[PDB]
Length: 129
Image (cartoon, rainbow, N blue to C red; front, side, top):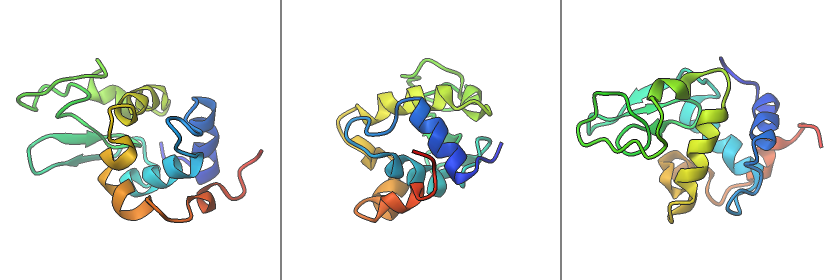
């Protein structure tokens, strides 16, 4: 499913991402916008033959198993297909693991290049307090 902006903000906030590891809700919404356009079914192949899955484009090289990424690790202990559900619970739990891994949200290349240092508050303007 394709989330609305405020719909996704409310879901991310309900699952505890607002200021998780110090990253305000606008950072997560912005990241989702540029990784997936808010589309839980988004899949994109990386040059190394891994694939990124879901609303936060979680990568099969380290975090989920898709059975076709040699050397895969599956640190979130999930099939990558579970990251495409209309329920973002698995994506958010896995994102908590990723962002705690030491490098913060720089793990999401699109966040580093398109959200970092920008007015991310704009991404939650209109959601309900």
